[PDB]
């Protein structure tokens, strides 16, 4: 639907993020033309957030819990599950499909 | 995480006569940075100016407010914290995890008028 997850590197296949859990990921976002618009990897600063509570775009809220701990995957997100038709120009153009590289580094106190 | 709205720093003056009005198509070279100084976006690095209509909501609120305050050829820095929607406090972030974004802006053109 609005977001598809495609695995790249498997995790422990046991620990999955649940609602309320605080998740720690390293990511890179790209538009459909292949150009990068944001990356935590470039800053060497992993991003931390609660995941079941709509604190991020739906693409992350739905996609991330489908990953296991230590998994690397690519989240392909429609504008609907993303920043919509408005977007956030010039940072993110309107009606943009987002392709994230995502690495789940931690779930609560797991790592 | 203190800032609110838009703060405009004047770096270098333009011609001081030609300001973008509502509906004008504007040419801009910009660099986006975080509060710590990290660069996350740049039209300069793409060697191609960002072109958009101004004052019609085709860019974020902070830009529609800040850009018409510049004259043709002006260099300025826009410290922007969205009041509503994506990127604002209480909303899902555009650049996780921030709300205040800083834009170095050079007004290169107003319609067919070039600096």
Image (cartoon, coloured by chain):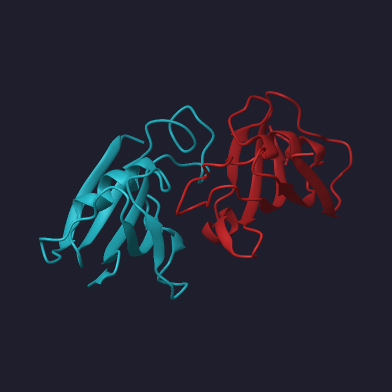
Chain colours: A red, B cyan
Residue found farthest to the bottom: B47
Q: Position of residue B37 (x, y in %)?
A: 37, 57
Q: Residue at x 20, y 50 (%)?
A: B69
Q: Quadrant of the N terminus of chain A?
A: top right
The residue at the point 62 percent across, 36 percent down is A57
Image coords of residue A64 (percent x, y):
74, 39
B20 and A100: which is toward the camera: B20
Return the x and y of residue A53 as percentages of the image width and height: 64, 24
Extreme residue toward the right, this view: A13
Compare residues A26 and A89 and report the one nearer the observer. Answer: A89
The residue at 10%/61% (across/down) is B16
Q: Quadrant of residue B19?
A: bottom left
Q: Count up the numbered dots.
A: 0
Residue A63, located in which quarter of the rendered image?
top right
Question: Is the residue A108 above or below the residue A93 in the image?
Answer: above
Q: Position of residue B4 (x, y in %)?
A: 30, 34
Q: Report the residue that reaches farthest toward the left.
A: B16
Q: Quadrant of residue A68?
A: top right
Q: Is residue A35 left or right of residue B107?
A: right
Q: Nearer the viewer, residue A51 or B12?
A: B12
| Position of A48 relative to B9 (above/below) | above
Q: Which residue is rendered at x = 63% and y = 41% of the image? A: A82
């Amino acid at each position: 639907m609005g977001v598809t997850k495609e695995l790249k590197s498997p995790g422990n296949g046991v620990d999955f993020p649940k609602k309320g859990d605080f998740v720690t990921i390293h990511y890179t976002g790209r538009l459909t033309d292949g150009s990068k618009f944001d990356s935590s990897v470039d800053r060497n600063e992993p991003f931390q957030t609660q995941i079941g509570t709509g604190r991020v775009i739906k693409g992350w809220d739905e996609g991330v819990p489908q990953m296991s701990l230590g998994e690397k995957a690519v989240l392909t997100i429609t504008p609907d599950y993303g920043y919509g038709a408005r977007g956030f120009p010039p940072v993110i153009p309107g009606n943009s499909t987002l392709i994230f590289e995502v690495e789940l580094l931690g779930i609560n106190n797991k790592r």
